[PDB]
Image (tube, coloured by chain):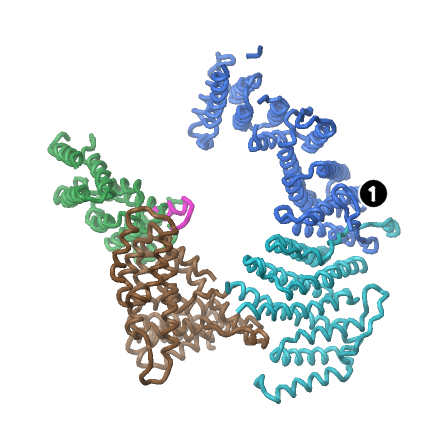
Chain colours: A blue, B brown, C cyan, D green
Amino acid sequence: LAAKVQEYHIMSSCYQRLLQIFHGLFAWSGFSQPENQNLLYSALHVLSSRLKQGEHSQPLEELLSQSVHYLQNFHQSIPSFQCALYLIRLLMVILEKSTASAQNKEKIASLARQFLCRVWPSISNDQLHALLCIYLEHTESILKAIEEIAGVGVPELINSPKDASSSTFPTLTRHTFVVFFRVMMAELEKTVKKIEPGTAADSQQIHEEKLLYWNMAVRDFSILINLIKVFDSHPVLHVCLKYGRLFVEAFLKQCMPLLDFSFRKHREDVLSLLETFQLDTRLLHHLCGHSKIHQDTRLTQHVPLLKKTLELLVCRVKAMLTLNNCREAFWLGNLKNRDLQGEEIK
Amino acid sequence: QQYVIQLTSMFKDVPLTAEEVEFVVEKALSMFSKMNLQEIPPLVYQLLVLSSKGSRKSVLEGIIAFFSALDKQHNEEQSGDELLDVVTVPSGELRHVEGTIILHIVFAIKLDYELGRELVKHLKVGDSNNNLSPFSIALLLSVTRIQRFQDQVLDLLKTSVVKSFKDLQLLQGSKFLQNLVPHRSYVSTMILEVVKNSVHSWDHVTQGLVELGFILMDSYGPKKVSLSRMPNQHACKLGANILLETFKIHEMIRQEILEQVLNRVVTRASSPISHFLDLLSNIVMYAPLVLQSCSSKVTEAFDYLSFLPLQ
Amino acid sequence: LEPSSPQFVQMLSWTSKICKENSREDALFCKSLMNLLFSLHVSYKSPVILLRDLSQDIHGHLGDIDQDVEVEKTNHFAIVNLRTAAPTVCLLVLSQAEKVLEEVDWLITKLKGQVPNQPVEKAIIMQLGTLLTFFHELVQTALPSGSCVDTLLKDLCKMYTTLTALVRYYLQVCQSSGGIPKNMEKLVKLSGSHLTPLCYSFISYVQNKSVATAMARVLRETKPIPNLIFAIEQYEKFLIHLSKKSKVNLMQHMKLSTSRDFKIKGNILDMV
Amino acid sequence: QEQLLQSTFSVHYLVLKDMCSSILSLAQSLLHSLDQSIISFGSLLYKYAFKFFDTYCQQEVVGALVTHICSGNEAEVDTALDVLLELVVLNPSAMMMNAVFVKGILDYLDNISPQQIRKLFYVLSTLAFSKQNEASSHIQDDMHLVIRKQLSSTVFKYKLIGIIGAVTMAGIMAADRSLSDEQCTQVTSLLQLVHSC
């Protein structure tokens, strides 16, 4: 059908149901035990035969990958979005059989981007969250993908006829932007959390690499909060005001010691890092004040803990300064409260 | 006011919703005073065997509140000159119907644990927990005969008495707070009255009572080997009072109390055992009473006396 | 002595008469005497007036934090001398205030679990309105940077937690839509215009002017100011809840919360 | 593991039988958990305790299992019923004389879900149809009357219980083994009776 709708709407549901059956069959706990490993091998052989048969006896890796290449061919034409998510899930459960995952975690992510960039003519928020969570984790250099999505989100808001949200990501609208924001910030928090510094025993290259990684992380975090100025609605504001607290807690907990260790060797980088984070925390304070200017219980519910773990950072910066015998260098001062757009309220 | 016993047949087979059963149990609560004292236990049996498939909190709450109020009224208006005076139903009838009803409730709880879990969660304590009463304390003490609820009710009783003694120690320590509030019956005298009231020929609470006494003594003994010591000392005093009180009244249990006290006091561990020693000296004051029941445990305690150190 | 007799009253009068008369250099003697006075006076009425008119005298001797305020010292108690007030009396009066807050919070939780709630509310409001003058009086003192300022921050956090418990109880009560009388309104407005901004002005002065166990001690320092900020913000949030419930507004009286951002200097080059 | 407890109950059963009441109390206490490993361990503890100990402790075991079944909680009911099934298929003769206690459960048929009633009738039937009982087959001819008096009732719920029990007992009575005798005629008579009722 590259070049009456009852049959099309029936076969679409059949196509979705079929891959649902496949995913249900290929993802049960019995395959963990080695009793039915022969049954699993026979099923994989049945799958892989339709490419090129002739060798019943084969290594597991070879026919596993051949079956995967067979199933990947169905991305040529599928009619819905649920079908695409199910195909991705089935590929996900099949590929984890192989021990090595050097290339699989990249091919899955590339296919997921190929599905997400497809226009999908007519989609619901409960499924796009899962698909974008699959895409966002599997790419290497998560911060690069996050920053790229943030830098291609602006072709929407800069020039869009009303509801004609055709960006270079054709599934970025004014009704589904909050899902993108939520998964983006959640994945940023998750990938930040798992970093760990230790004992400063490594060479200068390791420390400079970690500082560079953190500099990229905080730059992207600033560019991800900064565009809530133009998108000020209840759910996006709520999700940013929650996961910003989460990220600040992660930054204080995990990479304050790494800030402690290398103050001697690299003092010019860390100070600029703190100023760059200070700008973002200033805007977060502006958000915290704006949340209570207009009384709204559901959004104000989170501001006490945010204020606590955002004064914690200032006091811990003072603690870091005192740890290296430099107490006299600390100097405080209040700040002028601003609105979200930036003014001087009185 | 005569066909209420057969008024329960309407809620047996047909399904109902919560509002109408709540209304009829409210009517039953309002007519508890009207019907009779003696007719209550069969009605309680009928409603409680109905309650498995329907309302379960309401009936238990109503029974507990009614009997707490009746006990409170009888206790308040019972005091007076030993002469002709106004009184409601006498003690010999009231304690007996309370015993039958508590035994029936324990049996019904044994038939389905959900009622017992609802009862335990209902009487959860910090807070005053004003629903505590001699009847409710007796209930909680008699549920301990089931293995599912033993620790879950003993720890609640322990924290309750600790909270009460903390309240007393806080209230006696100031004038302003003492000036504002009127005193409420603190749960120490509540249990100390339940043990005395237990003379009326029911024994299904003695085991819970002695177990509570021993737990409450062990958990708050003087471990010296300053503010929190005063509740921790009043609790031990209450435990000793409770144990000595159940020693005299009930006969079947006095063989095991002395055995436990001896088995806990004759040790080489050199742990502080002053309170157990004081209790043992207090309960061997009634020398013939020990000789009637348990004259053997002291003998093998004597046979072991050669091994212990000098102190 | 039984706490109702002419002898008890004359004994308390005699101890108060000494505490209003003489001056002694020793810190132990005055601390024992103050403990004696509070032990007598705590069982004859609430000491909440004594704390106010004692800390008002404490505030005179040390000085304000603004560096340009002419206090009057009011000479209430002669035994609270210059060398007496700094490490000894302030810590003790803070402990006594913590005891008073414990009593008030027990009253509040008892009365909330109760549901005669007409006069008890007035009494609690009276005590809070009295000791809030105490806290407002000794916030601006230039206390020594030892443990006394940390104790003050801990007790102030306790005060705020108690007051939010009271506001929560009024949330639980005002479901009748008319349970906000004037005695609460004065308390809330006065708490807005006396204590809350001065907390921030004090925190500015506290922060500004100054092996593994060293690291543990350093991390031990960082708790009280964030704890206080969290308590204050929780208070304002529950106040917003109460304003949304019964259609009145209370955030008119108290201003917008100021916010803090650390700075730095290029004076670490002096270190090397 | 479980061969550890197997050796425990195999070698030192004579000394361990002194405090078997405490053993049963411990098993009863730990059967009230939520996972499956602890519950299975307590189940096999009951089983092994019944296997080696004295007849009085066997009576105590079956009493504890009966009160477990009538307690009410679903996991306890299923576990205790499975324990009884494997216990009666393990040592039918010792369990045979204690049929009174297990039959006494049948008075409480409002605390048990409909599905577990079939399992209860199954375990009771396979208890009452071992050929060791043919010397004095009383449980079988008692249950043929219990089922009749259940089916001839007027309450609908007991009629449903009766049809469930009659079918699941006729199944065991006409079980295919390694017969074609008068027992088959009795099976036929029971089926036409329960069809007419």
Residue A272 in picture, x, y percent from top left: 81, 42
Q: Nearer the viewer, residue B175 or A77?
A: B175
Q: Is residue B51 left or right of residue C266?
A: left
A185, above or below B175, in the image: above
Subunit under mark 1 = A
Q: Residue at x 79, y 66 (%)?
A: C142
Q: Secondary structure at mark 1?
A: helix
Residue carrying label 1: A268
Residue B14 in picture, x, y percent from top left: 30, 46
The C terminus of chain D: image quadrant: top left
Q: Is residue A207 visible?
A: yes
Q: Is residue A103 visible?
A: no
Q: Quadrant location of residue D192? A: top left
Magenta residue span: D32-44
Alpha-carbon neighbours of circle 1 within 10 Å: few (<14), some, or many (≥20)?
A: few
Q: Residue at x 85, y 65 (%)?
A: C67
Which residue of the protein is positioned furthest toward the bottom in this rendering? Answer: C7
The N terminus of chain D: image quadrant: top left
Q: Is A90 inside the magenta-drawn segment?
A: no
Residue A192 in picture, x, y percent from top left: 67, 39
